[PDB]
Image (cartoon, rainbow, N blue to C red):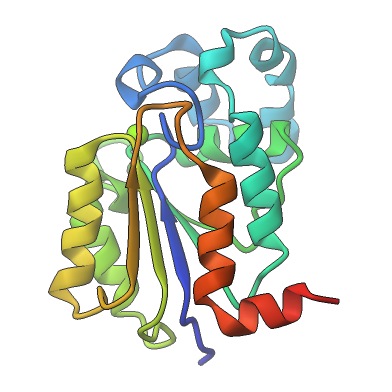
Length: 196
Ligand SMILES: [Mg+2]
C-alpha cells in the first residue's frame, strides 16, 4: 500500500557526518547513546555532542540537505543505511533539529542480533522488494567506495538501477547542493510540488 518511486540511500558516518564510522563506532559517546531509546534520554547528550570535535557532527550542508529533502516527502523518500546504532543516528538528527519521522533507518543490530545496516547490499535488496517500492530515481551517497558499491550492487540485483546517481566522496566533500539539483532535475512530481 502506497507508492515510493524515488529513494535517497545515505550512509551515515562519514557521509552525513564528518567522520568515518571506524573512528566513531567505538567512541564513548556513540557507545553511551546506543542504549538511549527515548528522545528525553538522548537529548541529555546534546551538550557533550556540541562540545565534541567538529568532525563527528552532522555537517552543515548535510543538515540542510536532509531538511530540504524532508520537505519533498512523500515524492522522495530518505533511507539511512548504517553500521552505527539506531539511537546514535536518531540522537544526532535530533541534536540538529532534523525531523526523522519519515526517514527509514537500517542500522546495526542490538547485541548478538544482526541488524539490516550491517549488510548494505542486503539492506537495499530488501528495501527494493517492499511492495510499495517502484522503479524510478535513485541517489546513493557513501564515503566508503566498497560500501557504496554494495548499495549499488543491491539496486542492480533487483533491476532498480536504470536511473542512479552514485556519489562517493571523502567525508566533508559531498556536494549536497548539487545532489538536491539532481533530485529536482530527475523527479518531475518532486519539482512540481516544490514550486509553490
Ligand atoms: Mg560511512
